[PDB]
Image: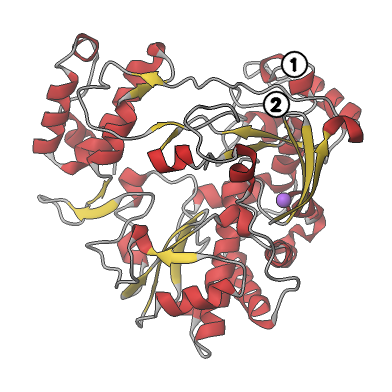
């Protein structure tokens, strides 16, 4: 991903986009009951905590483009992945506007809280004014489609979230590229059934885990993996994607019956953005945030891993490559041990910056004991080993509970954390509940006890 140019939006006929400048995150009733070191991300150039230029920091993610064309390994990767997907008999017909808007089997309805993007954001027109979830009305939307069409600019927002001290001082805040409601709708109409087919088939065939339920899915993963596991993290995955990777994705889509609408991928690859009073053009880089983002990042990941294995290990049997991606996150396996370090090396030549799994300093062997997926470990249940617990460490949960974005969602926020934490065991869970109940706010919450969550878990399979 590389920014071609950037300039005042007025110079190209666009209005200044108003974005919030004050975080919605404030210390919660548990701020001093639990240990934590993260704070709200810098949202503006004037943030006192900054120790470097903000604008420069937030756009530096666009490391550039390392490859122009789709090489022979990539083509091979494309044929193999496309072949697997073929086995799912994915419905290739476009999805009607009604479902693309209000959802259907395998596809949730459009999120009414998220941005409507340009130009609605500049006309103060919200989604709540465009769609009727109880009416399933598509006339207003249809009229808007006909009026403003598609391929509209994406609106760049700084993500309001918790970040480490270092990242705050270095202005390393993450960005959200909200596509226009029109594009989101047109895209869900074009790829709606693909999205659904993926949501309904999380696994090693789609090579995707998007739409999955960790509590149930974790028990299916081990059975799908080959003997030897391997993994690694990416640095700035989305932004590092070169145009070739988008072209490789289009080839996959063509081969599975969607060659009919690969043009929509161009909108993602070569895209223009609106940020504050500026407008810029980017070549490459996946717009982090758009409808389809995680699924397409996941598909491209399947292409990347395959490409690197072909490039590094001629004769590798991709039919025994068992991997599951969630955007840039990935858990993979092969009957034989592979060198993540070597793969990482091959990765550089493809514009990908790969590093040791889970922030390690060196590339160590990945095992069922130390592997994580979506920040969760895998732990067989003590009483019924065939049931696998997705275990997220208490550290991130402690960090999260120390802040709130709205006092009205305190019980939902805390219940949410409880569904994640109890998997760490009863001793830990009870310690967690006790601290919560050491302050008034917590004692007033309705939280499930351990045995209740355990029973609920067993009854969910
Ligand atoms: Na782009």
For residue 37, side relative to residue 433 (left or right): right
Mark identifier at residue 125: 1
Residue depicted at x 55% and y 63% = 301
Could you tell me which quadrant the C terminus lies in? top left
Mark identifier at residue 326: none
Residue depicted at x 32% and y 65% = 223
Residue at the bottom extreme of this rendering: 315
Q: Foreground residue, 61 or 232?
A: 61
Mark identifier at residue 116: 2
The correct choice, above or below, for 90 with respect to 338 in the image is above
Q: Secondary structure at mark 1?
A: loop
| Residue 57 coordinates in the image, percent (x, y) | 58, 44
Q: Secondary structure at mark 2?
A: loop
Could you tell me which quadrant the N terminus lies in? bottom right
| Residue 117 coordinates in the image, percent (x, y) | 72, 29
For residue 153, side relative to residue 86 (left or right): right
The correct choice, above or below, for 296 with respect to 137 in the image is below
Nearer-N-terminus badge (2/1)? 2
């Amino acid at each position: 991903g590389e920014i071609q140019w950037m300039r005042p939006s007025k110079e190209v006929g666009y209005p200044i986009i108003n974005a919030p400048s004050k975080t919605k995150l404030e210390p919660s009733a548990f701020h001093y009951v639990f240990e934590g070191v993260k704070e709200p991300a810098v949202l503006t150039k004037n943030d006192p905590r900054l120790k470097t230029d903000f604008e420069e920091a937030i756009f530096s993610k666009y490391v550039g483009n390392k490859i122009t064309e789709v090489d022979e390994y990539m083509k091979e990767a494309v044929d193999h992945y496309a072949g697997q997907l073929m086995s799912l008999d994915i419905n290739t017909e476009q999805m009607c506007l009604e479902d693309a808007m209000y959802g259907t089997d395998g596809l949730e309805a459009l999120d009414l809280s998220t941005s409507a993007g340009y130009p609605y954001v500049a006309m103060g027109k919200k989604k709540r004014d465009i769609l009727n979830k109880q009416t399933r009305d598509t006339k207003e939307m249809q009229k808007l489609l006909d009026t403003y069409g598609i391929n509209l600019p994406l609106v760049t927002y700084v993500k309001d979230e918790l970040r480490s001290k270092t990242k705050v001082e270095q202005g390393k805040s993450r960005l959200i590229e909200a596509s226009s409601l029109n594009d989101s709708v047109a895209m869900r109409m074009a790829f709606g059934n693909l999205y659904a087919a993926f949501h309904k088939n999380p696994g090693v065939i789609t090579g995707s885990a998007v739409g999955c339920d960790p509590d149930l899915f974790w028990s299916k993963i081990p059975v799908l993996m080959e003997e030897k596991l391997f993994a690694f993290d990416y640095t700035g995955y989305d932004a590092s994607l070169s145009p070739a990777w988008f072209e490789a994705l289009k080839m996959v889509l063509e081969k599975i019956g969607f060659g009919d609408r690969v043009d929509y991928i161009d909108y993602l690859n070569h895209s223009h953005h609106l940020y504050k009073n500026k407008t810029y053009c980017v070549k490459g880089g996946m717009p982090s945030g758009i409808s389809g983002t995680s699924i397409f990042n996941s598909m491209i990941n399947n292409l990347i891993i395959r490409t690197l294995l072909l490039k590094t290990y001629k004769g590798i049997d991709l039919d025994h490559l068992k991997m599951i991606a969630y955007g840039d996150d990935v858990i993979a396996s092969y009957p034989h041990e592979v060198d993540a370090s070597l793969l990482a090396q091959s990765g550089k030549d493809y514009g990908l910056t790969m590093t040791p799994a889970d922030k390690s300093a060196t590339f160590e062997t990945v095992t069922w004991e130390n592997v994580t997926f979506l920040k969760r470990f895998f732990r067989a249940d003590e009483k019924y080993p065939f049931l696998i617990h997705p275990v997220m460490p208490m550290k991130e949960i402690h960090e999260s509970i120390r802040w709130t974005k709205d006092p009205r969602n305190t019980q939902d926020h805390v219940r949410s954390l409880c569904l994640l934490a109890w998997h760490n065991g009863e001793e830990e869970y009870n310690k967690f509940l006790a601290k919560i109940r050491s302050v008034p706010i917590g004692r007033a919450l309705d939280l499930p006890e351990y045995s209740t969550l355990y029973d609920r878990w067993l009854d969910s399979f």
